[PDB]
Image: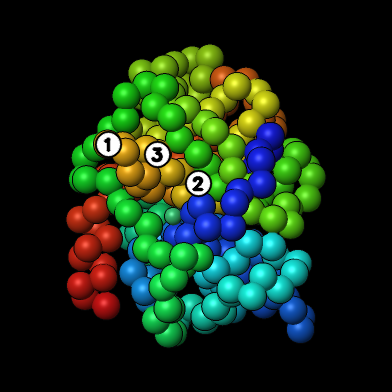
């Protein structure tokens, strides 16, 4: 997250860190949202590589013992069947991970609430992106979870020529684009949390930013629209 602030330890308890085995260590690569005690929602592009993955729930600082972490291996991966790694603009950037164990819930570990199917936020709806992604374009990952306030940009504006044009689809949510704050590499797969009727719900799965930079004016961060996949998610969990 570029232009973010440090999140309070218990603000976003559904946020997880998706990590891969690297030598004799683990490295964060993407975020995710805990949606069942044994299921995580992330971006399909985060699991394109055939690596060993684990999820960390109750994580706050990637480099220090928080005293709240639960480490769980990824036992099964179900990527959306229409995802194509060489066509992120087509959408479908979503995947579900079944965990080897069911995590224990507490104030640092809770399920993410999803929006009702088909819900579309009005332009300029207030949301926060959270993640440990780069804090500057071509920078480094954050040590502590960051949050940035990114208002939505509706489809009509987002798909206009000066914004994302034909790249953005109605199956995506755009947010931000002020040139100061945004998601960045390493935030992919994580949540876009938006307050609706007094409750936050996870409306987006971070998918992509501009090749010209994370924080670029009129290139809002683009997320997979969770509300376009409610039936898909329910169907995967029920058959797995
Ligand atoms: Ca930690
Ligand atoms: Cl949360």
User: Which residue is identified by label 2?
Assistant: 206
Q: Spot the residue most to the right.
A: 139
Query: From the Cβ of disc 1, is ligand 2 less than 8 Å away?
Result: no
Q: Quadrant of the N terminus?
A: top right
User: Which residue is identified by label 3?
Assistant: 194
User: Which residue is identified by label 1?
Assistant: 197
197 and 81: which one is in front? Answer: 197
In the displayed structure, 118 sits above or below 163; it is: below
**Which-is-in-front pick, marks 1 and 2?**
1
Separation of marks 1 and 2 at Cα, in angstroms: 23 Å
Q: Earlier in the sequence, mark 1 or mark 2?
A: 1
How many numbered tags mark residues here? Answer: 3
Query: From the Cβ of disc 2, is ligand 2 less than 8 Å away?
Result: no
In the displayed structure, 190 sits above or below 160; it is: below
Q: Are marks 1 and 2 in contact (CB under 8 Å)?
A: no
Residue 66's tag is none
67 and 32: which one is in front? Answer: 67
Residue 9 visible? The answer is yes
Specify whether 72 is left or right of 36: right
Separation of marks 1 and 3 at Cα, in angstroms: 10 Å
Specify whether 162 is left or right of 60: left
Quadrant of ligand 2: it is bottom left
């Amino acid at each position: 997250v570029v232009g973010g602030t440090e999140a309070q330890r218990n603000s976003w308890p559904s946020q997880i860190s998706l990590q891969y085995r690297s030598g004799s260590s683990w490295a964060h690569t993407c975020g995710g949202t805990l949606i069942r005690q044994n299921w995580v929602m992330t971006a399909a592009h985060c699991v394109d590589r055939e690596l060993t993955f684990r999820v960390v729930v109750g994580e706050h600082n990637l480099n220090q013992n928080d005293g709240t972490e639960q480490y769980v291996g990824v036992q099964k991966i179900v990527v959306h069947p229409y995802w194509n790694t060489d066509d992120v603009a087509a959408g479908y950037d979503i995947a579900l991970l079944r965990l080897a164990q069911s995590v224990t819930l507490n104030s640092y570990v809770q399920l993410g609430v999803l929006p009702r199917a088909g819900t579309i936020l009005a332009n300029n709806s207030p949301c926060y992106i959270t993640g440990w992604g780069l804090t500057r374009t071509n920078g480094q990952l954050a040590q502590t979870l960051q949050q940035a306030y990114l208002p939505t940009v509706d489809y009509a504006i987002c798909s206009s020529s000066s914004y994302w044009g034909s790249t953005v689809k109605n199956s995506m949510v755009c947010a931000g684009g002020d040139g100061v704050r945004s998601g960045c590499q390493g935030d992919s797969g994580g949540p876009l949390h938006c307050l609706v009727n007094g409750q936050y719900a996870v409306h987006g799965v971070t998918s992509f930013v501009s090749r010209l930079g994370c924080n670029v004016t009129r290139k809002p961060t683009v997320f997979t629209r969770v509300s376009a996949y409610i039936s898909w998610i329910n169907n995967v969990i029920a058959s797995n």
